Length: 529
Ligand SMILES: CC[C@@H](C)n1ncn(-c2ccc(N3CCN(c4ccc(OC[C@H]5CO[C@](Cn6cncn6)(c6ccc(Cl)cc6Cl)O5)cc4)CC3)cc2)c1=O
Ligand code: HEM
Image (tube, rainbow, N blue to C red; front, side, top):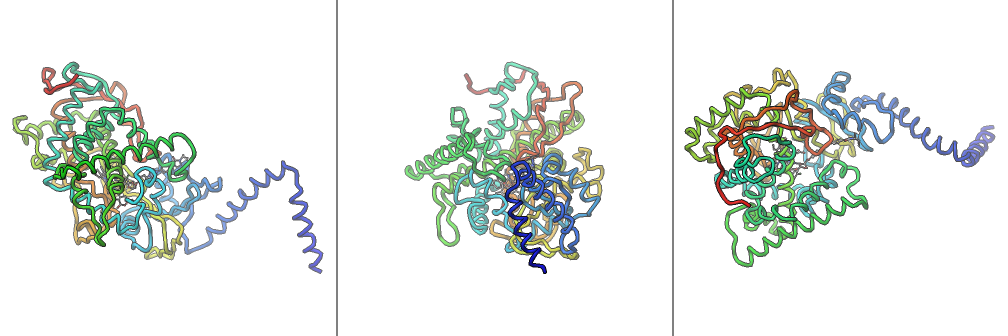
C-alpha cells in the first residue's frame, strides 16, 4: 500500500502549514538556500553549459565580488575555468567570454541572437527619454547613430577646436579651482574639475552657445539631478518612489524642454545653420522609412549623446592627469611636441595640427588602454547560442558579458600591461584602426572583425561613434593643460585605483594634484566678473 504514504504526504503538508512563525521564517530562508546549492551541484553536471561560479546567497550571486573588482574576479574565474564561464548577478545569469574570441562572440553576434536594448534600456530610457537609443528597435538606433555621426565630421571638428579651446581657457581664468590670473599654483580634485570642463566643452561645441550659457544659471542643477539617474542601480531598480528618482524625471523633462524650446525657436526664425549637433539633427533626422524624429526625440537624443560623452570623457581626462602627475618625463616629452608642432606657441591649435601630435594622441590611447571606461558590456541572449568549438549552449534569457578592458590589462597582449607607457603606441597613434575588411550596419563602414585585443570603443553594430569627438575634446584639453601647467602629486600620493561600481571606471576620490603655471606671468584675456 502506497496509499498510506500518499495520505501522510497530505498530513505532512498540513503539519507544515501549521508550523510556528519561527520555523516558517527559518524554512522561508533555509528552503531556497538549500535548493540553490542543490541546483548548482546539479547544474555543474551539464556539459552543454559553461562552468557557473559558485555562490552562497540566492539571487544576489557573485554581485559583491564582481562589482568591487571585476577584473580580479575575471582573472580568478579564468584560472579555474578558462575563458568562458557564467555567474549569477542580482537575479540574472551572466555568461562571460574573455579575450579576443569573446569580443567576436558578443560584439559580432547575430542581431537575432542578442539584444543590447534589452540589457540597457531600463537604465537609459528613464534618463534620456522615450523613443531613442534603447527605447526603440535596433534599426532606429542604427539611423540615430548615422544622424549624430553626420554632425561629427572633420569640418565639424575643425570648428569645434577653437570653441573647446576657448572653454578650457575660460575655465582656467574663471573657475575657483584655477584662477590663473590670480594664482600661480594650487591644488585641485580632478574628479571636480574634469566633469565641469567636460560638460562646459561638450555643451559649447555639440549644443551651442545658448545651451552653454544655461550652465552659468540654476539650470546647471538639472544636469546634476539628471546625472544622478545615471547609476548602475537603475539596472535593478529603474523606478522607485524615492525623491532622487523624481528629480531625475523632472530634470529630463526640464532639459529636453529647454532643447525643444531652442529647436522650435530656430525653426520659427528659419535660423537653421551648421553650428552644432542641434542644427544637424534639425536638418537630418528623417528615418529611411520617411518617419521624422519628433522634437522630443531629438531632444532626448541630445541628452543621451551628451550624457554618454560626459562620463567616458571626464573619467578619461582625469586618468590622463593622474598618470601624468607622476610622470614629469612624459609631461616634458609632450611639452616638446607642443612646442614643435605649434612653433613655440606661435601657431594657433587647429584640428589638423592636433593630428600632427602623435605623442599626445598616444597618451590618450594608452590611458584608454589602462582605463577602459566601461568594464563590462552586456547583451541579453534572445535565442540559444552555440559557443563555437565547444559543446556549450547559452540559452535565451541568459546575458553575455564582454570585457575588452580586461584584455587591455593582460601581459600576453600588452607586455607589462600594468605599466603606463605611451611609447608602446609609437608609429601607431590612431584612436583605432580597421585592420582588414569593413562592414556597414547603418552608420558607416566599420571594421568587420572585432578580434583586436585593444577595443576601447567596442565593435560591431553597437560600436561607439563618439571616438573622434572624444579624441578632439581630450586632445584640445590636454594640449592646453600641457602648454599652460605642470602638475604633480601631494607627497606620498599616487594613481588611485578605479571605482568599478560607478557607471564608468572613474578614479576613486578624492584624487588631488598640485598644478603650477609654466608661465606665472601669463594672463588669460577676456571679460569676467
Ligand atoms: C549591489 C552590491 C554592489 C557591491 N554591487 N554589485 C554589483 N555592482 C555593480 C556591478 C556592475 C556595475 N556596472 C558598471 C556600469 N556598467 C555599464 C555602464 C554603462 C554601460 O553603457 C553601455 C551603453 C549604454 O550607455 C552608453 C555608455 N556610453 C558609451 N559611450 C559613451 N557613453 C551610451 C551609449 C550611447 C549613448 Cl547616446 C549614451 C550612452 Cl550613456 O553605452 C554599460 C555597462 C555595467 C556594470 C556596477 C556595479 C555593485 O556595485
Ligand atoms: C573615451 C571616450 C569613449 C569611450 C571609451 C567609449 C566607449 C564606447 C563603447 C565600448 C561602446 C559600445 C557599448 C556596447 O557595445 O555595449 C560605445 C557606444 C556608443 N557611444 Fe561611446 N565612448 C566614448 C565616448 C563617446 C562620446 C564622446 C559619444 C558621443 C559624442 C559616444 C557615443 C556613443 C554611441 C552613440 C554609442 C552607440 C551605442 C549602441 O549602438 O548601442 N561615446 N562607446
